[PDB]
Amino acid sequence: PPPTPPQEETGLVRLLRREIAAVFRDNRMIAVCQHVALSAEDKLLLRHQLRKHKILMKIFPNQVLKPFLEESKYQNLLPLFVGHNLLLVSEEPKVKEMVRILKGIPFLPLLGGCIDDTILSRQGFINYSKLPSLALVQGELVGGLTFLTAQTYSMLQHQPRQLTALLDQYVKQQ
Amino acid sequence: EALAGAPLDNAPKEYPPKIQQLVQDIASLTLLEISDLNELLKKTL
Amino acid sequence: FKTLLPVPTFEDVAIPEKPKLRFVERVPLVPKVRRERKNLSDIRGPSTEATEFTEGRFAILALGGGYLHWGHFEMMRLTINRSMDPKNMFALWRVPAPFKPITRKGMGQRMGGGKGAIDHYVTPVKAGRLIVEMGGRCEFKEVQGFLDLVAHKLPFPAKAVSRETLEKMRKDQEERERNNQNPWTFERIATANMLGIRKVLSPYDLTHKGRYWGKFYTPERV
Amino acid sequence: FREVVEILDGKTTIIEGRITETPQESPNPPNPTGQCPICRWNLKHKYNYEDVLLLSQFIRPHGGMLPRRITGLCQEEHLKIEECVKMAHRAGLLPNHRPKLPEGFVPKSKPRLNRYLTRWSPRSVKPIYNKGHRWNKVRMPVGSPLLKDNVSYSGRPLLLYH
Amino acid sequence: SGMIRAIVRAGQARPGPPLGPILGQRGVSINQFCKEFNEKTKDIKEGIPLPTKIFVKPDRTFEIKIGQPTVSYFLKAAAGIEKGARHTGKEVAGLVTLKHVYEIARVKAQDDAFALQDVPLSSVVRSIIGSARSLGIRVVKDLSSEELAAFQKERALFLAAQREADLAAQAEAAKK
Amino acid sequence: AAALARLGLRAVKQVRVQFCPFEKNVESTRTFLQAVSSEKVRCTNLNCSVIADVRHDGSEPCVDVLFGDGHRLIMRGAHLTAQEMLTAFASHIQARG
RNA sequence: GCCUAAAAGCAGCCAUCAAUUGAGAAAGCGUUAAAGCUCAACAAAUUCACCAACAUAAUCCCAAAAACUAAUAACAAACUC
Ligand SMILES: [Mg+2]
Ligand SMILES: [Mg+2]
Ligand SMILES: [Mg+2]
Ligand SMILES: [Mg+2]
Ligand SMILES: [Mg+2]
Ligand SMILES: [Mg+2]
Ligand SMILES: [Mg+2]
Ligand SMILES: [Zn+2]
């Protein structure tokens, strides 16, 4: 064949690229699910139940999403965008309500996604949802750090406490 | 640059090396340094 | 997925008043009292006048020769006026009213005795002539689809063409006649009087170049 | 090649896909610059209804044609190869490419008439009863008109109608 | 059976067509449906239409979902004109304000469609403006002291002359 | 999905599709899953149970269809076309149903 | 939105806006009117896909026949040697 007549980028594909870039740069939770062909009423009901938690959904064509993803650092998501796709976009990720609202529908499975640049599967999302909060784990960090000295002091103070316990046992026996 | 290798829990055995090197940095310090770090953490957070 | 292509927008095309076709008379206001001869030169050969677009954009091009009378005029008028859009489309005639008289005789009359009586009037049309020329803010596919019926019902073979289609077919004709492979061409042979073929040919063949034979026009003959 | 295997085990159907080994293309093509398979193997205007080894490369085991999007041939040569396969099937070549019916192979019928270079179908042509005169002759077509551009070592055109 | 869309008045739900034969073919009773509709819309001003969706199950049972009244009715009421204009864009039917448009949006947002769709009041206001321009009613920014009556007298004269011309044209067509 | 919509899928109990989204032969599997989870299949019968099992290290997609004729159709579709799986399932449920 | 008994995208006339990533006050089927079946728009893929085909008379159809061995062949007059 003759040499390639190279194609030009159009305004629509430029807008799509800019939108995908803004999505992947701004928000934190980017979940990838299989867009199930459901009725429009149920789709709007799910829209409302997601807007209650303030997590939105987007849909991008594969012809514009595959090249962007294979060019960016998210090339590990290529086998996820083969069929129908749905990008759940959320700021300040809270996967608990998302898993709860997807449990109510049996044939709508969570494929995967990234939570703060951490690509996880469905089991990874389940583990992240069951995991405690950031404030709670930060409060537990210092506790687990000082637990060594706490157990040290406990062992140092339990020696006089053993006599007290034996004395209380002898009192209770009589 | 690139992102992580997309791990899962079915065969989870590789942990971030930053955690291990931070644990080593903690364990390679004396008790007074650990007390200073704990005091600074309790004051800030 | 599919890229959105822009739609052709028309704003400089001004739709004139009375966009539909006008009424034509079967016999003109001044009927010819003197009977004329049926010259065939008005059909033989290519058309000399009304071969280009004036104000319209589509047209009914006749690839042959023949006669058009009040019946065909009424057919075309009714069909176009009922299948056109007077708000976005306008039409115009490219052929005048029927003026050439035709003589007829009643059955049972032997040959001779004089000329017949003027029965009706017709309009001579040559090959390569436009019949109806239309314009407006419409596309080419719909006007072609709705004018192919009239092109079929016309006596001579006709096609619903436009400026672009006519230019394209003329460029194709020029390309074919200039890249033809055989060194022997009808025009060259007739002009050089090769093989004494002028005994069989006609003096009008020197101009027709073997493309026009009687009333038929074959565009695939270089 | 992919094969669908079905197993019946107590009202339970097991349908599985099995991939076998398929032979690849020969290593040295005579004209590697051609995009089409035949046009690059320089078999254009070379094959015919007699060449069975070439036609048998792309046909289903039940005599079916292989799709163009999977084969890769140019449109003209694909149509020519389809015509050649039809003509070979009608002529009686490719004996191992018919469906096996043990119930229908028993009731033998009238012997198959020996034919070759047939254009139409054996059950869709009506015999010519008028046959025409010399000037208006109803010619009997033989062979496909798509193969009129074959190389003629004898130089004479191929009689497509006789 | 499935879903059926209907637009009936508040309390004027009669068991005749064009509502009778539908539920008759479906299977459910007509008198029972009319009684349910009247007892559910008894507090509504009788005379206004409101859309309803009837979900009929295979066991000849039916459930009703009523929405907010017709936006065409809302606009006709806010304009004070009973029947909208004929030649939309060529003639003026009524005159409403952005205040009335926002009020209609606020009172109609509480419906099934705008409840399923998490849209702000701006979308509903734009839809109301579109429906008003379809009806032919002009929407001025803020002009209502007497201009409403100044246009109303001219609209009344226009509709009176229009009715006279319609009667004259009907008589002419009958005589021709 | 129109085939399963017009075939009358009222005679099925449970349909489960077990797959791993991080494999390289899940195209036909997810196509079949969407074709059987379309809205028309749902409105054809509401007593059926559609389940989509998602794993990460299974590496073997499968489809299990249990229907009340005491029948269990198991299709380990890892290389089969989605259309082939659909037509085989349709023929089987039409023959036994 | 008007007329009509009904005109719910479609006897008709006028407007042809408005949200969703995305759906025309609707380009054909269908009802008396509905309902319902489609087209185009998103998400799923993306072989080629614009028009071109048409019976017939009378005694009995009328050489048989042949798609590939090389052809600016050959056979072919009251023409010319
Ligand atoms: Mg004609
Ligand atoms: Mg929008
Ligand atoms: Mg479509
Ligand atoms: Mg007949
Ligand atoms: Mg004979
Ligand atoms: Mg001789
Ligand atoms: Mg002599
Ligand atoms: Zn080729």
Image (cartoon, rainbow, N blue to C red):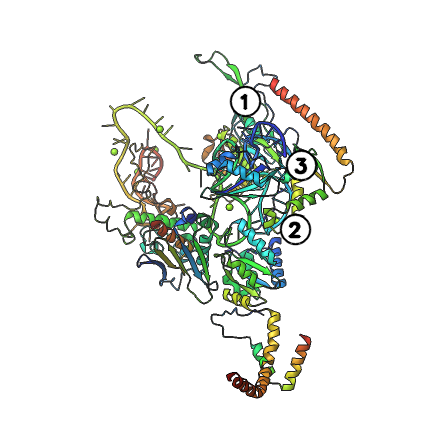
- Residue tagged 1: C70
| Chain ID, mark 1 | C
Q: CA distance from mark 3 to mark 2?
A: 24 Å
Q: Residue furthest right?
A: E145
| Chain ID, mark 2 | E
Q: Is residue D154 visible?
A: no
| Chain ID, mark 3 | E
Q: What residue appears at the point 50 percent right and 66 percent down from the top-left corner?
A: A123
Of badges 3 and 1, nearer the viewer stands 3
Q: CA distance from mark 3 to mark 1?
A: 55 Å
Q: Of the residues shown, which amino acid type is indicated by label 1?
A: Trp
**Residue A83 x %, y %:** 49, 57
- Residue tagged 3: E76
- Residue tagged 2: E120
Above or below, C146 against B26 in this view is above
User: What kind of element bears circle 1?
Assistant: helix
How many residues crowd mark 1 within 10 Å: few (<14), some (14–19), many (20+)? Answer: some
User: What kind of element bears circle 3?
Assistant: helix
Q: What residue appears at the point 65 percent right and 81 percent down from the top-left corner?
A: B37
**Residue G30 x %, y %:** 47, 35
